[PDB]
Image: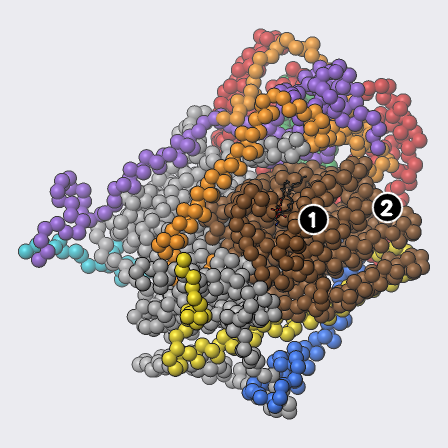
Amino acid sequence: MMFIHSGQELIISNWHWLTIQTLKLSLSFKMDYFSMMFIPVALFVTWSIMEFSMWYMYSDPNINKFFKYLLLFLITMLILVTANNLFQLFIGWEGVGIMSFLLIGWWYGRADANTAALQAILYNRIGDIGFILAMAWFLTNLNTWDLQQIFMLNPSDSNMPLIGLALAATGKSAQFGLHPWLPSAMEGPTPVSALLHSSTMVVAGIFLLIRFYPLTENNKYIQSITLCLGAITTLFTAMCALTQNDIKKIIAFSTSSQLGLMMVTIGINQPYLAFLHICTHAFFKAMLFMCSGSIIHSLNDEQDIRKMGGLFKAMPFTTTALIVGSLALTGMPFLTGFYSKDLIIEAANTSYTNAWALLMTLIATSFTAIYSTRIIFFALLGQPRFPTLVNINENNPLLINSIKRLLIGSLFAGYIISNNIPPTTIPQMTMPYYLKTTALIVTILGFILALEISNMTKNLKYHYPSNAFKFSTLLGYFPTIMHRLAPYMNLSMSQKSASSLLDLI
Amino acid sequence: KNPDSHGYDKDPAVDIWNMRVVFFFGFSIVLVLGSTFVAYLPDYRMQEWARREAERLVKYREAHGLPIMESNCFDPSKIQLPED
Amino acid sequence: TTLDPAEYDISSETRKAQAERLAIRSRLKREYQLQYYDPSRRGVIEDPALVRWTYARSANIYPNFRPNTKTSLLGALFGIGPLVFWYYVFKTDRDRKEKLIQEGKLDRTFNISY
Amino acid sequence: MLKYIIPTIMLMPLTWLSKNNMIWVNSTAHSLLISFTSLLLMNQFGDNSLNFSLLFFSDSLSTPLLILTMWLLPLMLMASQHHLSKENLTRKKLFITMLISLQLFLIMTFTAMELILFYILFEATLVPTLIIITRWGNQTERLNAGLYFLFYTLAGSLPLLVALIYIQNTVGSLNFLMLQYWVQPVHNSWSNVFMWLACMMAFMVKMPLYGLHLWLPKAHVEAPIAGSMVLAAVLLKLGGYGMLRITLILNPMTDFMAYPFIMLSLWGMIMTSSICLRQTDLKSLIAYSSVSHMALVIVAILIQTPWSYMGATALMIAHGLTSSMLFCLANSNYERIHSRTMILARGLQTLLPLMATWWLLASLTNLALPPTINLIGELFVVMSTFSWSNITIILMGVNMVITALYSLYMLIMTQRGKYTYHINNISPSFTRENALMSLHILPLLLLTLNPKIILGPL
Amino acid sequence: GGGAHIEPRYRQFPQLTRSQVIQAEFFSATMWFWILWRFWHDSDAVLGHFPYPDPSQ
Amino acid sequence: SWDKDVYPEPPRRTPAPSPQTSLPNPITYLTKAFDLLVDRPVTLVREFIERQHAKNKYYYYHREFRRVPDITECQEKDVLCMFEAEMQWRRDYKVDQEIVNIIQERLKACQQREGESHRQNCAKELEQFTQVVKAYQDRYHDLGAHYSARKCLAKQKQRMLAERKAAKEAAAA
Amino acid sequence: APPLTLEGIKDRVLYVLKLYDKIDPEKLSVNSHFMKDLGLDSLDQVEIIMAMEDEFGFEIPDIDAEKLMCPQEIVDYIADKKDVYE
Amino acid sequence: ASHITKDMLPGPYPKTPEERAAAAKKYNMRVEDYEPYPDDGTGYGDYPKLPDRSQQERDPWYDWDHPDLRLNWGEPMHWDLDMYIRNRVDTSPTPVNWNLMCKHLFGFVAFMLFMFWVGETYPAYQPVGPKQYPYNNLYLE
Amino acid sequence: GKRLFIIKPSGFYDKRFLKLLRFYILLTGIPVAIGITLINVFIGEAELAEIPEGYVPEHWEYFKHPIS
Amino acid sequence: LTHQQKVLRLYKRALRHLESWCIHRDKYRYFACLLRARFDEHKNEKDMVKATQLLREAEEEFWHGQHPQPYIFPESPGGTSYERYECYKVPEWCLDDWHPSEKAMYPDYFAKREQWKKLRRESWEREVKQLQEETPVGGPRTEALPPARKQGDLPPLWWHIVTRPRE
């Protein structure tokens, strides 16, 4: 509140770490517009998240140390948003990239679990290799990395230094071509991925590029590759979503394609309207996952979309949490993110856009319906199907206490956050016909094609298990060969040659 | 090496002596008592001296006439400069 | 792509005289469990296939080697080759970049570092 | 100065002169004390470097580097104790003497005041090290490690003494580094290459290039009990710093031929770390780390232009510890299970829970998380060596990838279920197991608080 | 052990707590009441209409 | 504090109040509250020692060297006389680093002091700043000999090129 | 934590096996020897474990099929898998 | 302290039946096609007689596979052949050798041409010729 | 009633350890701790100005700090 | 595998991949007999090549129509949260290194353990030597006489008989 009166952001000069030749790096913090709003949010969710784990992990003898592992994560992810000293951004950049390993790797054995770690730290390290390039470029040219100074003394050619950044963006923002890591990043504990994927760790990839707005506004090369990238991420995730059988997996891709809209908004120059999205969005998918807890646990487990049943069997409240949020993510009719996804395709959509993303993105908006309605209709709709002796109890003070806070802090949220801002830009506000509800226009028939096809999937005339189709769809088919290849063409070729084959000869 | 003795290094006694002779000599007298030394140890590489003297001397020139950061080659016409 | 991998082939009935391909292995898993079940052991097992796995791999080549076949003189295409290349790439730079540093000034005057 | 050599030689009859088994604790007690003297008059300047005597300036130089050298001694007797308790005392009195007999020269060297005390003391080891490798080996392949350790180190370091006696009588006197205030350059000829090549190649054969390292894993794979002298031989190697005293001067102006030492070790840096992934023997696996991000300094030193010496110094003592400490883990876990074969030990991390966080903090400092010394020692490398030519970002950018798969595969191999047949491995790391494994991560990370004490002059 | 407080189900469809669902249903209003002000007062687009810039004179 | 003309800054321009309104402002229930839970445990203690500290006053002086040694002294082969002619030159290369530090921070005070304009104000620092460092690496920076710092042997052999080339070979001058 | 006993497994297995109209619910339950109700070679042994997986649901190993002669034998070792009765 | 004849000696053949199995039984009968043969393309000292190679590939598959242990955990007594790539490799997929990904990865490459155009919404295409005029064409005032 | 038997390898040799640090690392820590505050309370660095100090000031001890 | 039972391993999985294709619980159930019809079409005929075309062409039309991401029965050879709990794994024989004052707890349990060992302390003289009588030379699968002819103690003691539980 102190800021939303007088402005007056701050930093701090504190403590001099070593001072080499000329550039003197000490440390600092940044109170800026991304600092004032977000940080309360990232703590507010995590306020509600641990209670859930407090019930979920309740029986684990090592629980005491769990909250330690989960604690540093929040700490050091919290110093990424606040640091104006470019080096200092890199302390927590990799401080979090290790935390993934020490969480996804929770369960030993489970030959998949600890090989989902070695993924996370393989793909981030490539995505590392960029952001150390733009860490070098500023010295040899500008003789500082201070985020203040670059913005005061503007670089002419950002072409090389910036493209490095767009590469480190894609590492942690789960963009296309680095994507195969998320769907297998879910193999750990449930409240983990709730924390990993909601407001944290996936946001830095498209976060960092925002911080660079003042310098990036020029040089169409920059803007060009962005929206020539993020838009494409969507339909390889969407086209890979359908047919997938797990509660957790579909909720993984749902946040995978939430990205494509964010990164597009950096492509057209929309610095703030991109970031407002995450502030709003993060309230969803923590709930949405944390909802599925009582579904997985109290069913003793399945986390398959098969063997689910219908909407009401002793799940009155949690099933209201789904159909609120899982409605909200659908294009926000009056709800929370009504200022997030809705103010994009109606604003930046008047621009130089590639005339493909317009085709491409708005089509992805459709599947936002069938994302939802699928995992709604197999879990909340059909007849009960699952083995007998099901003990379900939802009366859980240490749970119901958690959901109730979010959904309340959900509906009111989108309007409170949005209503109070100093306006930073000019939206067009003159929106002709047929450009108007063109998102809503698509979702309207999404629900149509949701239910008509749902009944056409199950309730239909018995379209047989006809063996012939093309599924490159449910696999994605990229995770099939490459992960059979990259650990061949390298490990067994440039080593077994280089090994005692040569050095001993 | 456990006949249900506790033990650290070798045998009955000085083993017990051998633990206090490492722990106590090893740290709390060095990793602490010593670490204190260089913590506030005096100005290292004469930089402390430099901040102020590279502070005072800025304005002295800036005050009257003089430029800032000359690099005039240390008073030419002290040098005959062989041409060819 | 990599590979068929031949999950069906010809068979039936030829090479049904081939038996005791299991007698080879069945002997050991009898003997191995005859090894592996004993009250007093407390220790690892010889497992020769591992002894002959490294020692026939790391050592026992330069002994076996002969410098003859020109597919073993191949390595000049591998070992030295690109090491010349990286000289060809660099030595052009560090020069092309040098010539300009003399005639003409590419940099700015706020670069002190270096 | 004599403040140091005299007590540390006074150590020498603190040992045998003693009684029976009191010996170990007797000398470990004192050997720590000298560390107060170590700092004592040291960590003076700073600017206009300290030279307190005619033939010694102990270390001024901003290459302090000597404080470590005095650490690792009473880290040995905590390290070396395991299976050396099984033979006689008059031999155990020896192994503590020659081990000191090493520690006495490493104080002499790093000071040396000059070139020609360096050399005769640069070659003055190999008398004490060679005797620790051949005796108290384990396998019978040791006998060849005895030779290979010579016939390189000594092989090309004789061309020093042909060259350094060639300078002594050419220009003035080499008697002192601190007078180079007359140095003419080296322009070119078919003679001067050799001079520069003779004054160099002796040093390379210690800190390996990707050629002529053929000895380094031969000596480490098979080598004394505790790594007892294997901790010391990871000091010896990095002590090839003296190339910092020469190549700064004394033929400054030939960079002409630098390139065969750049592109030869710069493509090995991306290389020999990659031939380290399929290794089946653990004390091999670490031995090839030691080449890799050591051999990065050789592209730091040859390039001039500090911000390399800012980053080249931090590296000599960067892995000086991390690469030390790993040989201390792989020793311990070997006490209990007598194969060094990496496969065999699996299903740990249940049975030795406290030693979990010991592997981690070790294998985390090859990853080089940003705050520690490691990166702040690498990111002054990349900043200057980028300006050399922009393309260095790729290969040495790849180094920062394969090294991460490199380290983890060593830890994550020890997270599995294995109960399997082992009735051994009962001992839950008696204190020395975790005591000597500390006094590394405590002092290591610590320096990041005031890390102006590890830096060159530039 | 812990307690019997609820027994499981053989697919006899277990009973609710009767304060479970009502306490929730009050949050079925907060979407249906907070959707009130959508059309009141706001239309499909509150804009103003571009009047076809005929004056090319 | 510090020396004013060593660290000049523009004045405060405190903003005028604009209540305009009939509604309560919470800050006045905090700045009137927060102040009363701060000053007591805080300001009393700083006053507590600062008098407790009146009991003793130390001294540490302002260290100023004695400059006889010059740059043209003295012998060619000499040691004694050319030992010092760096001590002049070495300190005076440790100064000229830091004078770039001080002038750099003064730049930052052109931005977040303002930051909205960033352009139409300050009149000075940037247009000066790149007239400073261009007075730096020339002749005060021995490059690429910066590894050796090549003190006074190469220090004047840039500046021979800054003599034996400029001002004469410039053709015609 | 869910309480498990040896009664239900005698009941549940008795239960669905008594649910199938292919079997009269006067027939033996604990011991029929199942070879009287093995008809035919297939479509019994693997047929009966098709449903019994739908309730407990662990994997029903292959080589454990030939233990299914005795109706007390099937229930016998299902105690040893899920850690059942004392 | 295994005394004599620890590992492979100078093969590929001396008495193929002398090796497997004297000790180190790769084959039972000296022909299992596990005979210490696979010295394919020799003169490379690599893999001498070796009660060893080309025994087949793609994984130990790590499933029920339960005589005792049989694959990656539990260590059957002695089969070991080739390893160390086996903890990052598995078996047959459902389809076979269809690169439709290079198809789809180039699927957008169709829309490269969609890049050379623009998306400007207002006005429409309205087939034109010389009507385009991004900024101005004729006189200013 | 419904109950089991926990299994852990050993807690004692780890708990018998950490003490010898935490006990000793304080033992000379805390006495070194007062001297970093008390010694600064009554004694601190002041001030400047200037001084000619007559012939020459003292030797080292030109520093501004309690112990420096 | 004996030629008789070779259809079982198909007959086990045949309907298995079916159900993950069907959705409604009746859908699986309604196609049961209907697809069950095809098995006994030729119920009794030759074991060899005549009916090997019931094995031969079973290959295709199965693999064709395979991988609709089957239901994996979570704790099993594959699929999520199968081998999940290793954080206990019950390292049997954790009872060695203690330094009592850690052994004060469970006194009744320490009493019970040393009572188990007496069996394994000496069961051997006829336990091991009978295996020298039992298997004449090259014997296949290695278990003893199922009783061991009077009292097995265990005999397989205790590694298989006392082995680790799941929680």
Identify which amino acid the numbered label 1 is placed on: Leu
Q: Colour of chain H?
A: purple
Q: Which residue is mark 1?
A: D161
Q: Report the side of A43 relative to J98 (left or right).
A: left
Q: Nearer the viewer, residue A171 or D307?
A: D307
- Image quarter in which the N terminus of chain A is found: bottom left
- Dividing the picture into quadrants, the one containing residue B32 is bottom right
Front residue of D97/D354: it is D97
Q: Position of residue A428 (x, y in %)?
A: 25, 58
Q: Colour of chain I?
A: blue
Residue nearest the observer in this picture, D384 or J136 = D384
Q: Secondary structure at mark 2?
A: helix
- The residue positioned 51% from the left and 19% from the top of the image is J60
The amino acid beneath tag 2 is Arg
Q: Colour of chain D?
A: brown
| Residue at horizontal 86 percent and vertical 19 percent from the top | J136
Q: Which chain is red?
A: J
Outermost residue, front direction?
B84
Residue D121 vs A82, above or below: the answer is above
Name the subunit of mark 1: D
Residue under the image location 14 percent in, 51 percent down: H136
Relative to C34, does residue A298 appear above or below in the rendering? below
Tell me the colour scheme of the image. by chain
| Rendering colour (chain E) | cyan
What shade does chain C have? orange
Mark in the foreground, 2 or 1: 1
Residue at point 29% right, 45% down? A354
**Residue B26, percent from left and from top:** 77, 64
Q: Colour of chain G?
A: green
The residue identified by callout 2 is J113
